[PDB]
Image (tube, coloured by chain):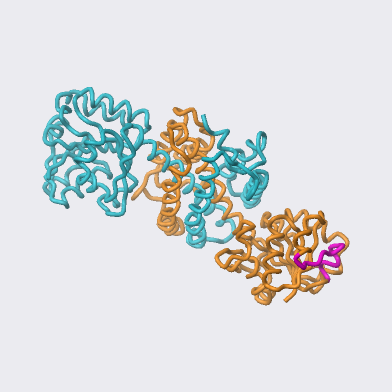
Chain colours: A orange, B cyan
Amino acid sequence: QSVTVIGLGPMGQAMAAAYLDRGYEVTLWNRTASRADALVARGAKLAATPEQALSANELVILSLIDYDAMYGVLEGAEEAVAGRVLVNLSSDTPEKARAAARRVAELGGTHLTGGVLSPPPGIGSPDMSTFYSGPRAAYDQHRAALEVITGKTDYRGEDPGLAALMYQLNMVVFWPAMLSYWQAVALADAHGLTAADIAPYVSENFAGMGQFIDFYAARIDAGNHAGDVDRLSMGVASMEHVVHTNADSGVDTAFPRAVLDAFHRGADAGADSFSSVIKLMKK
Amino acid sequence: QSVTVIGLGPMGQAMAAAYLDRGYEVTLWNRTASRADALVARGAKLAATPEQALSANELVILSLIDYDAMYGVLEGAEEAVAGRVLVNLSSDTPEKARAAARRVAELGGTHLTGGVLSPPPGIGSPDMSTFYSGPRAAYDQHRAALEVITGKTDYRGEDPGLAALMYQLNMVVFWPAMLSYWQAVALADAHGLTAADIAPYVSENFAGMGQFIDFYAARIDAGNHAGDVDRLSMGVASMEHVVHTNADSGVDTAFPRAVLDAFHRGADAGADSFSSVIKLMKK
């Protein structure tokens, strides 16, 4: 059909190209015009202002830095928001997504919050996924168009903060997982091992994690933090060994001591399951 | 055939039962005799001292607290060590494994270091694995017997510290991965979501991690920490959002700030790839 893309960083440039690849009439906008060059040469239309970019289509795809940058685009484009569906793909907090949705509805438009679980070359893949939250009717109406961004789309609820929350929940896991790999690479280095040497082991470790999360999910939800299969004190001692191995090799112990600190703190409550630390993390 | 198991905590009790299940003539020892009860009732023989436990067989399986506890068992059993293969499965540092091997060889015996990647109910499973390091001839001779402990056995090298290193490399990843899950559970709680609600998402996230580790392994080993697919500054900002989301919900920010701290530190070098922090972690 036809669509608008505002924000042409690597994410938005990949979204526009996926829309052009699918035969969509594409209208664009970016603060730096020289980022739309390749897209314009392919047949995308560059708007001179955000107003013209907005009023060109009912579906408007936003891929800006954050929600704070979004208020700048809309700063004078007020009337073009009415009767339009604004899909905000800028990864920020659930609170900032709720404040963005509230302002858009006030302007007579609808806000869909998106959490894209894809790097830019994954944009348009049938295997990638995006979390969506906000008004169900707008999600349903434009679902086929959001499938252009990622083949899979996952509607979480009416709450604007929901897709943002899911996005953060993902990053809570990803960043430390990758950082634990940077820690593994650094230790294995002081021992003549390369990153590709430990890659199969680390991949296999992450691949088998789901068995543990399912086993633990059932016990947490029931309120069971036993000693049946594991004890926190042994976790503390295992982390002391990880800290010692890294310290012995001259490798930095900042990330492993941070993990040890959470286990040591907790034993001060308790030497039940290593899951018991959750009760110290919750509000 | 016939075998000895010293140390009857849940790990050693599961090892002895796997040996009895396979028709092995089993000789035992533990500091607390009441932990061998069930095993003796099944046909295992309880020794009165470590000396008698050692001299009963050429293959001796050790499952003690650590290497420091091992010197106590051997404290007066000196002569029973000669001509015996001692498999030390006590998870401790590579340095303590090298000091344990050195003492055993001095006593005329051979030390095999083991790193069991299994909880006690996984003991004897064809799907589980154990890392082994030390003299190749002893590993080769007794491989069928070590397959009773875990179906898969992975000989890493002649170095006593090697299997211990591999064991730590595993724990470097496991403990933070599980802790990131405890962090995810805590955040999702302040938002009406259960652990089983987020379990599929977290499992899927870990399952897809191997793609990232393989992509990054090749670039690290070559010395490439570009900006091609990612920038450290965006990682810092993404972690700031994870920290803010948790702080907004009243959830503890200790584990996410520790991750943010490693990214923020690093940008002080550099805003190339988020992999660039490795050069600050190495010796």
Left or right of A84 on screen, residue A223: left
Residue lying at 30% horizontally and 39% vertically, measured from the top left: B132
Where does the image place residue B196, in percent across and percent down from the top left?
47, 61
Where does the image place residue B273, in percent across and percent down from the top left?
62, 43
Is residue A140 visible in this depiction of the protein? yes
When asked about the image quadrant of residue B69, the answer is top left
Q: Please state which of residues B30 and B277 is positioned toward the viewer in this rendering.
A: B277
Q: Is residue A205 above or below residue A6?
A: above
Residue lying at 74% horizontally and 59% vertically, measured from the top left: A99
Q: Please state which of residues A228 and A64 is positioned toward the viewer in this rendering.
A: A64
Is residue A223 visible in this depiction of the protein? no
Looking at the figure, which quarter contains the N terminus of chain A? bottom right
Q: Please state which of residues B256 and A84 is positioned toward the viewer in this rendering.
A: A84
Left or right of B228 on screen, residue B30: left
Where does the image place residue A34, in percent across and percent down from the top left?
80, 55
Left or right of B58 on screen, residue A1: right
Magenta-highlighted residues: A42-55
Q: Please state which of residues A261 and A113 is positioned toward the viewer in this rendering.
A: A113
Left or right of A68 on screen, residue A18: left
